[PDB]
Amino acid sequence: SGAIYVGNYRVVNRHLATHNDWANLVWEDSSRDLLVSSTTAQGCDTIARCDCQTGVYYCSSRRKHYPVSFSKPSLIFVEASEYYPARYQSHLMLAVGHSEPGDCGGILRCQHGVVGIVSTGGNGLVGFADVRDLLWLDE
Ligand SMILES: NC(=O)[C@H]1CCCN(C(=O)[C@@H](Cc2ccc(F)cc2)c2ccccc2)C1
Ligand SMILES: [Zn+2]
């Protein structure tokens, strides 16, 4: 679990969005596994606006942060799960690292701010949904 809180927005994995997220829906994209909802309180997270390919992510299944080198956001095949049929997930970045069910929502950060959230894993890999292209989160 986990979310990004920036301005009057909450960014979560679309497959973990709650009834309240859908009632206050701003934007969602099944191909990216992202959903953004509106909030009443101000969020203070800073979104990175950069092309960093190194950062640190939080892994809830280890209660630890790990440094990672990750690929540029791209279209990657993701196997069928109870949440989605087999498909290409867009804007996904892969890295070598531990990730298991329950880790989605952990933040990946670089020196500039929040880069994205855990969205996929297994086999010693971890996949992050990028949020750096969503410039409207800042306004
Ligand atoms: N973005 C997606 O489509 C996710 C949705 C949840 C599932 N998902 C994952 O990759 C799971 C692994 C998994 C489990 C059962 C399956 F039938 C297929 C794959 C996972 C997420 C996070 C960290 C480690 C593993 C894709
Ligand atoms: Zn950066």
Image (cartoon, rainbow, N blue to C red):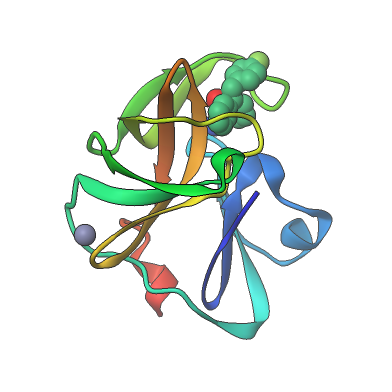
Outermost residue toward the right in this view: 19
Observer able to see residue 85: no
Looking at the image, which residue is at 22% across and 47% down?
A: 54
Residue 64 on image: x %, y %: 49, 48
Residue 131 image-quadrant placement: bottom left
Looking at the image, which residue is at 31% across and 56% down?
A: 133
Closer to the camera in the image, 83 or 55: 55
Quarter in which the C terminus is drawn: bottom left
Residue 94 image-quadrant placement: top left
Observer able to see residue 66: yes
Does residue 16 appear left or right of residue 62 in this picture? right
Count of labels shown? 0
Residue 119 on image: x %, y %: 52, 37
Does residue 96 appear left or right of residue 29 in this picture? left
Task: Determine whether 18 is above or below 39 in the image.
Answer: above
Q: Where in the image, quadrant-wise, is ligand 1 located?
A: top right
Task: Determine whether 15 is above or below 126 in the image.
Answer: below
Residue 97 on image: x %, y %: 39, 30
Residue 114 on image: x %, y %: 37, 62
Looking at the image, which residue is at 46% across and 15% down?
A: 123
